Length: 276
Length: 13
Length: 100
Image (cartoon, rainbow over all chains, first blue to last red; front, side, top):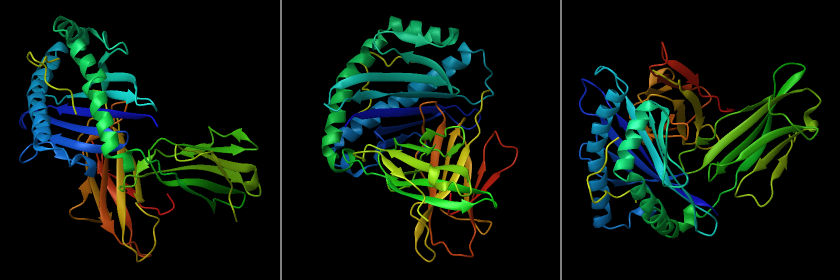
């Protein structure tokens, strides 16, 4: 199937409570495999999936050097952005970065990503060309000019097309039994009367991986988007995910409703009904 | 593997 | 500043069966900024030593965390998740409903 790798950096200032915290986590698809936290008693890159544990000491030290250096640079960046927005020394602020590479079903690079935010709003993004930037405002334009002057895009491109893809393919092979395994949802429909003339039908999907899934209700074959309650896909804690979709229907019309489920683990979409 | 450090100094925002 | 309040779901890892060990989860998501206080409650009292996932975030930059602890559900015992965040004037309590 298709696969991606992403790293997620969060740098958070906290005036009066020490230097800004830097935490990095790494993912292949929906599986976290590393972490680094500057607030740890002894900050170091730590494994978070069994298949990364085989990497040697040089790997762990290489990661740790990268994250320790980033910790320091992000503190400078937080100071710089405070200034670009004319902000006080009093408030706590956050820079986030997410970046990585997407591969298609053949293992070839589909595209790269490298996006940053400040206080939860887009700040600067590497364009799909991996060569130019989109800045969200005149503050981010300062960063853009600085990064253009230092030919930063060229560095990001070299990584995204090179080491990013190479290491993702390695992880996919080393973790093939899980990373390249799609677990289909286990499904059922429940029925709960809400009154004498209405009942809730809830369509459940449990135990699936990866998290991407489509769960919908149809009435007489028509999508019921507005009248469907859909919860956010949620982690079970055993690698798998859960989701449900509910609709409130007239008592006696239950058989006019069908739940449709699509998931990578499914050869063909499922259609389910309440089974009294 | 995360983005490696550049040959020159890592550029801040 | 722009802030986003947390979504909260409380649920079990496995389908709940009374008398059988399981995990109680509280998933908080969609929030910004990242500081957040989450307690799991058993009959109104804080459960000690609850674990949680490493801080990460979604494509829209909002943060998410999973808090979890082992538990053995029963017919009598009530479980809940209590959340506070800068966006909330008081802690929000969401009860565990095995049908949700």
